[PDB]
Amino acid sequence: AFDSTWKVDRSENYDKFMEKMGVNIVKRKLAAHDNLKLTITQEGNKFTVKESSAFRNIEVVFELGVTFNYNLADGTELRGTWSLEGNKLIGKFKRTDNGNELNTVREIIGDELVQTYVYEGVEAKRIFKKD
Image (cartoon, rainbow, N blue to C red; front, side, top):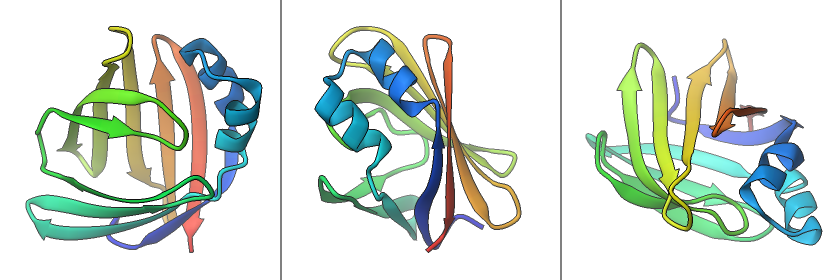
């Protein structure tokens, strides 16, 4: 349940979602073809999450309920919270570049971390397999 190495298998509508966020064709196609390995480690309420990719290796220490600037694969600065609700880690974010809302639902379907990303009202569903 969550605390393990999760790598991206299949990314569904993510270049359309990133076209509504305002990002260039080179960076937008590399954020679809990204190779993102998320190793989630529990620290003391906090989650120390090692985010290993073709762009960057970033260790993100988030507390359950804290308002922080989260950054994705290329360049998207998100002020907001990771909150635990009924299995699911709920990413309630908004762009500190804009004002617009971004909703990232982290959930385990058996042995797959399936991230549903909603910007304004546009769905993109990234399926992460175990390593």
